[PDB]
Amino acid sequence: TLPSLLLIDEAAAVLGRMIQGLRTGIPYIHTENDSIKANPILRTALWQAAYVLEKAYRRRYRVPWTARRYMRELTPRQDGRNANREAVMAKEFPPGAELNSDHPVQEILPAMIIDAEDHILFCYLPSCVSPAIMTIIDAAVGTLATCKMTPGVLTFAPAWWPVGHENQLPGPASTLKPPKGEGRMFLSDIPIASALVGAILAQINQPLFESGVKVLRELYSNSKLTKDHSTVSKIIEIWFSPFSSLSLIVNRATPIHRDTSGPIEGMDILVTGGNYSNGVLVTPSFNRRWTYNPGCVVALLGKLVLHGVPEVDGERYCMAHFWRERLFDAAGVPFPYPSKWQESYTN
Ligand SMILES: O=C(O)CNC(=O)C(=O)O
Ligand SMILES: [Mn+2]
């Protein structure tokens, strides 16, 4: 009875069917949900994502360690700045023969990196987002941000803890409390984009997608879980995403680092955009750089994978979709462990 969740559910389903079709050569079944079917921009964006993701599953680098063991050496707040600690990790967890060809060339083709037991650590999807959707995001960010976009970070979530309120109940993000403010407006401008990124997540880690949606369901229906539940409810009704949170990072370069808030096993999804030509995402553990230009998507275990992105020759923003495990705890949903790549093929 919550149509936004039902739309991202169908977007996930129909994109999976598109991928299964590309793999089998049999016509895929269209969605009868005409929020998708009658929306040419979202529909063709799902086609494009299907091509890129199918390209990525066919191009898999393996590191010779597991995510479990890597996670075990990690100190609770090992964000990547201790260079000595990082060189010790790097010896204990080297790139391996499939990756550490001497000095690495920059990747441009879609690909993924899986651990020793087939878990997806990193998924690189260049040009995964159609120009039309990138233009929707360009407009939304534009009107929100007014060098030509004022730098900064801005965070949105229907259920959240502000810094200093950790031990109270969670509630609407301050940026989203004004019902006609900048925040809500921004969310209202981007449901097609949100729906796309959530569908991509389903293709990479279906259980995590449906856990997230389950959590949003429970936060909607169960009032005793949050402050200001009326505002929580209104925001969930325009929350076209399975993620706990969305963060817009405008005109900022990013040092090589690890996230340390968020579950050690959560997969974030970054979408980069703007008008610049020399984007590069750096992953030292994988001995790799990845071309990182507007419309690129990267999914990654970001509390595990060191990643950074240098200054570029233009305006740039990044949309970062991520997780708060405490919301899972509060909603009675265990947080799932990272999916294996074969799960993509279990039809
Ligand atoms: O620079 C970017 O596009 C991505 N940002 C991050 O991973 C982060 O803030 O943790
Ligand atoms: Mn990050």
Image: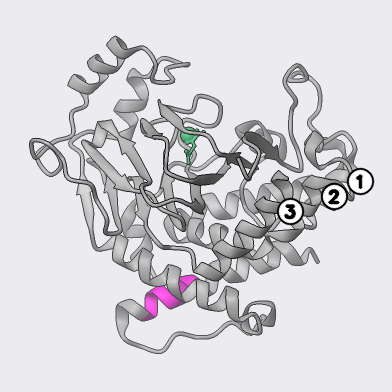
* Quarter of the C terminus within the rendering: bottom left
Q: Secondary structure at mark 3?
A: helix
Q: Position of residue 220 (x, y in %)?
A: 80, 50
Looking at the rendered structure, the kind of residue marked 1 is Ser
Q: Residue 174 location in percent, x, y?
A: 81, 34
Residue 72 horizontal/vertical position (percent): 35, 22
- Does residue 24 lie above or below 324 as drawn? below
Along the viewing direction, whichever of 308 and 147 lies nearer the viewer:
147
Mark 2 or mark 3: which is in front? 3
Q: Quadrant of residue 27?
A: bottom left
Residue 19 highlighted magenta (yes or no):
yes
Q: Main secondary structure of the magenta part?
A: helix
Disc number placed over residue 233 in the picture, else none? 2
Q: Residue at x 36, y 47 (%)?
A: 278
Cα distance in 3D space between marks 3 and 1: 17 Å
Q: Name the residue carrying label 1.
A: 230
Q: Secondary structure at mark 2?
A: helix
Instruction: Please tell me the numbered disc located at residue 187.
Output: 3
- Looking at the picture, does residue 191 appear above or below residue 318? below
Q: Which residues are magenta?
A: 15-21
Q: Amino acid at mark 3?
A: Leu
Of circles 3 and 1, the one toward us is 3
- Ranked by sequence position, the earlier of labels 2 and 3 is 3
